[PDB]
Image (tube, coloured by chain):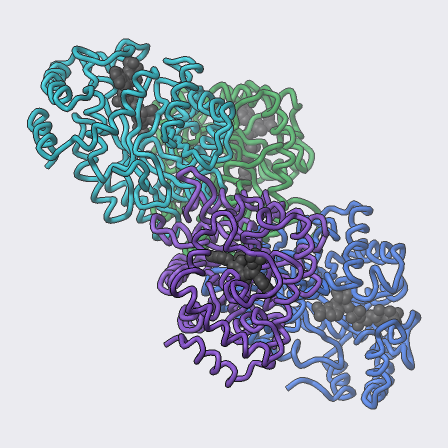
Chain colours: A green, B blue, C purple, D cyan
């Protein structure tokens, strides 16, 4: 295991684990909790912190920014990343047009109280904006020192390749990373497609929702000590998914996986996370945590890593029976 | 109907209707009226506001800028555009030379009290300036964050193509839009030529003078409630056009069109404007208004849109008998 | 005659006559005189004012800058140009290296109290600096808004072409003008070589020393009312040239030319200057003046222009017997 | 001999001798000593001063910066250079990634109290960073005015060529110089490889450790008046090298060289340094000095230069018996 690795083939070194701020900062948890969670993460070697202009309507960014100024950590020791797409109710306040990328990132930076982010991501694809406009815009903010690199999220392999094509044709800067969902019940893209882009154009993979929003911790049957999101304001969809006919099917397999965990001497959450890092293809996994206990338990997945043999992996595949092909 | 659409093939989303500031702001109407007209427009979904360094010798821009700071609307919810060409009596204070484009836009920005405009247009072609110099200059102000995009106005298809040629040869930024005159008595360019540029190089069309400066409202025989421009200082030309042998010919056809309007249950102005939006090729129509009544009547053209059948259109063509070919 | 014309094929319009500041501003004449000379020039339509970082060790630039702020003329109505090369006694304070072009122009701008000059010239060729470095540097200051265009001076046709080559190969900005010496006794370059560059690469010609530092006014035998430079501090070389065996030869021909002048009803200085403007190839002639009388007499050459027939020109050639071939 | 020469084929003129700041400024010597050493160097024509973000943890840069502001020397008369690579204990605080090059140089500039350095070097190769990212980053800081040129150090010929390749393929700025070790016991690279890069891609050579950290002054057997570094904190390696079986072998040859020195009428240090400048291929030699006596003795090597005949050189080769092939 390598705690720090390159994000894709770029020169940006990130910790294999990062702390995100979705649903948490400026929302579910208190600012005191947030400051505690980031300090723990930072003091434990994590240098990657992800946020977005849409999270808690900018509040997540403000909190994140406040913790950074309050703690006084050197900017050069942090790797801050934020996503852009949804930045307001006005028509021109969403998308990947040059206008919103400039205005959006500028706004996030003000809220974050930072001159620049290390990586600015397109939170998702934009059907209404030509790839050229977007790539120039991304290239622009980087040349303006508002960001060091840029990445994509929820983009198809072809779309990412199109970005690369545009960059090479007009001599702009290619994307260095894709933020994809990755957990035992969402594997195809990261396991089959992303490696392809890594070898062809050096694009790295930063994954999110290691526990499927908490579903994989088993907290909805055999879970670890924490709070509940499925029962949070506006997450009726999450509750539905969990209570769905299939929600029960996966919740059943977790029981079998829970076994392997005990057998390995770690919690289910730790198994699931270390599982995401088995991939050499995954540069870093973004953690989600509402309390210090969950965070440290998760950060413990690092230890579960060496004890993950090929047969243990194959055994996992059989239980999940969804290995990508 | 789509209220918001892309300006050409760019990522900039504009309202199908915009409010201009020619003859009005800083001139014909009072600042109080102006603030009232823009607020109405803004509150009704219009995000496109056009001006020019030449309008009322910069006063139009100042008023526009004052309304924006006074109202406090978010910059990211507005799409401001201004034209450059005539910026002073000095020899070097006019044209499309790098010198005037930089100095001109910089001046408009100061008067507008804005860091940048969304689109900066060349108010007209410049015979004395090489296309390369102009395109570099436009590309320059965009890279300097003084503007997000640039467009042309009163340029020929070939000239616009030449701009595009220059941009692709030296890797500069192509124009995204052409501001052309468009109303029932001026159709050829927008109906026949502009679509060609849209498909070939993604150039969009933003039209102006939907009512031919007021002539199409019939206010010079069967017009709507408002004031008179043809009788304004320096518009002797407009009065002449209206009193011309042909001025009477078109004023005659309006009578026939006025019929269709009543039949449709809308005013002549509404018919004429909704007529301009029938085109999928027209990204947005710039309105001209000296009072709140005219503005709301015009903004009503949106409703007249669905009730505009092909036969109604063909019937219009027969009355006008000028359909482009 | 066209009072204003394009500098080369660029979009920058200049007056056929400009006022320079060599030997004069911050040196030979008083600041009061300078302010008077520029005001006269400006009020008479001249918008071109040339200076250099070397002139009076920067004082010329300071004076020029002071007159501009004091008079309050709009920056957009002026065309300021300065040359760079000799900017200090330190090794790295001279040349056309990126370092000196940046530092040199930045210094001139501070002394001039201006954000930018319209044209920055290389005062002369640099053997110790690669053309690429120089062209990038020039391109750089233009993109940084420190200058609008750049030109060369005392460069050979080949050198200018090499600059153009570099610009097109790396997509940098080509030079738009060459500042060459031009008067009845220095003709070859401007009459034979410069036109070639104008047609091939649009390079314009801005000429200097219309009177050969005063020698052509005949003030050293049959001259106009003024002061003496040949007898100034450090111009022993000028005195020598005038007293040279050839100095007498040319001083003899002036006598014959003086005749043609009277015959035309103008002074010798006016003849000589209007002679420089007969060329369509000369965009502008930089005047040198130590007092208001000389300036207005010179500015009068404009009138002598129409009365300059082909036979009068041919008659001049015979007297000079140095027509270029 | 030419006291000032071009650094490689660039336009940057440097003194054949420069003063470095490794081990000295902010460390071994006092700030008073430092100010004295730089003043001597400056007053003697040296305009080249090298430092690094790693030297004395930034203190070297601070001292250097303080001397510069205190003395008030014109920025345009100095050639400041610093190296980037090791800038902190955090993972992302080292390397040649865009992130560290920007943050690192920005930090050095703050400590140096300067807007820019003349040349920013990569202190060494980075295996974890793609050449493209590095060259863009270097090109970026130059375009941002944080540096005038950039160079490499401890890079292989191939690596330097790869940088050049990247620059020409994406139209970025190539490196102008390589900082290589060079003294009588380290010759291969500077004598055989560097000339190759100079002719092929104009890369110049700036050498360091003319005395092999002091070993060549003979101060460890027959040395000049000064202090001892081999016995300094953390230089156990240097002491070891000197006491090594080979340390004695070279220390033996010095005895023979010491002879030639007396015969030439100069000190061993002077011989060794002037030896480094015999090369037309070496643009400049960076001196190391802990006191004014060493500095002036070294600066004296300039005089030893003319008295260095081919036979004297050949005689040196025989004693060293390591001439490159
Ligand atoms: N680019 C994109 O499209 C997206 C990126 N992301 C990134 O990834 C992060 C999101 O991960 P998220 O998706 O929130 O979640 P995870 O899948 O990592 O689940 C974290 C949630 O699971 C619960 N949990 C965590 N650890 C434990 C534990 N040890 N025991 C029990 N329960 C535990 C908590 O639930 P509770 O709160 O109920 O206590 C917590 O909020 C974000 O911060 C963001 O940066 C996320 C979504 C989209
Ligand atoms: N780029 C270019 O070359 C140009 C661009 N434009 C753009 O378009 C806009 C100009 O439109 P304009 O050309 O002024 O005008 P329109 O053709 O839209 O006519 C508006 C005028 O008609 C009258 N009017 C408007 N609505 C009504 C109504 N409902 N009933 C009766 N009369 C009515 C008013 O006359 P009155 O004032 O007499 O009451 C008003 O000033 C500008 O704001 C500008 O941004 C305009 C010209 C050139
Ligand atoms: N780029 C380059 O390499 C160079 C550019 N230049 C440019 O051109 C200008 C230089 O012109 P300069 O070269 O000074 O001179 P000119 O050839 O135009 O001669 C001007 C001088 O002649 C005398 N004079 C002018 N008008 C009259 C008159 N009507 N009657 C009698 N005597 C008269 C004066 O002499 P006195 O002062 O003795 O009274 C005056 O200083 C500078 O300002 C500079 O901008 C100049 C040199 C090099
Ligand atoms: N880019 C890179 O990788 C590197 C670049 N460099 C550059 O070159 C410089 C380093 O040179 P350095 O490598 O320090 O040394 P040198 O080989 O020039 O040796 C200088 C040392 O030798 C002694 N000395 C110097 N002159 C005399 C003399 N006349 N008589 C007796 N002893 C003398 C002193 O030892 P004492 O202190 O013991 O008195 C002094 O510190 C740095 O300043 C740096 O800028 C250096 C290393 C790496």
For residue A159, say whether it is visible: no
Give above or below for D233 relative to D56: above
* Residue B305 in picture, x, y percent from top left: 77, 70
Image region (quadrant) for ligand 2 = bottom right
Vertical side of B136 occupied by A154: above or below: above
The percent position of residue B123, horizontal first and vertical second, equals: 67, 67
Q: Please indicate whether residue A106 sits to the left or right of residue B315 in the image.
A: left
> Residue drawn 77% across and 81% down?
B312
Q: Using residue D117 as the reference point, say whether residue D254 is left or right of it.
A: left
In the displayed structure, D26 sits above or below C136; it is above
Residue at 77% across, 63% down? B55
Using the image as rendered, state which of residue D22 and residue C3 is in the foreground: C3
Horizontally, is A306 left or right of B132 in the view?
A: left
Of A137 and D115, nearer the camera is D115
Position in image of residue D173 (x %, y %): 38, 47
**Across the whole image, how many numbered discs are drawn on residues?**
0
The picture places residue C264, in percent across and down from the top left corner, at 60, 80
Query: Which of the image's four quarters has the N terminus of chain A?
Result: top left
Towards the viewer: C209 or A197:
C209
């Amino acid at each position: 295991l390598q705690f720090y690795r390159n994000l894709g083939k770029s020169g940006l070194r990130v910790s294999c684990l990062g702390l995100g701020t979705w649903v948490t900062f400026g929302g579910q948890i208190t600012d005191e909790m947030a400051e505690h969670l980031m300090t723990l993460a930072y003091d434990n070697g994590i240098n990657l912190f992800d946020t977005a202009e849409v999270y808690a309507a900018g509040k997540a960014e403000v909190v994140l920014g406040n913790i950074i100024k309050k703690k006084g950590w050197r900017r050069s020791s942090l790797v801050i990343t934020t996503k852009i797409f949804w930045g307001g109710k006005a028509e021109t306040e969403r998308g990947l047009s040059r206008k919103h990328i400039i205005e959006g990132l500028k706004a996030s930076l003000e809220r974050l109280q930072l001159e620049y982010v290390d990586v600015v991501f397109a939170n998702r694809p934009d059907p209404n904006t030509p790839m050229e406009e977007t790539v120039r815009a991304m290239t622009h903010v980087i040349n303006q020192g508002m960001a060091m690199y840029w990445g994509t999220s929820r983009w198809s392999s072809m779309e990412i390749m199109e970005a690369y094509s545009v960059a090479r044709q007009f001599n702009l800067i290619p994307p260095i990373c894709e933020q994809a969902e990755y957990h035992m019940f969402q594997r195809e893209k990261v396991e089959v497609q992303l490696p392809e882009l890594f070898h062809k154009i050096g694009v790295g993979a930063m994954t999110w929702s290691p526990l499927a929003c908490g579903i994989v911790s088993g907290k909805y049957d055999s879970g670890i000590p924490p709070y509940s999101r499925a029962s949070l304001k506006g997450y009726q969809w999450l509750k539905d998914k969990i209570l769905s006919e299939e929600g029960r099917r996966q919740q059943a397999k977790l029981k079998e996986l829970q076994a392997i965990a005990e057998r390995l001497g770690c919690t289910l959450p730790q198994l699931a996370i270390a599982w995401c890092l088995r991939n050499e293809g995954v540069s870093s996994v973004l953690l989600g945590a509402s309390n210090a206990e969950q965070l440290m338990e998760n950060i413990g997945a690092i230890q579960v890593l060496p004890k993950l043999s090929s047969s243990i992996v194959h055994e996992i595949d059989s239980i999940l029976g969804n290995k990508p092909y």
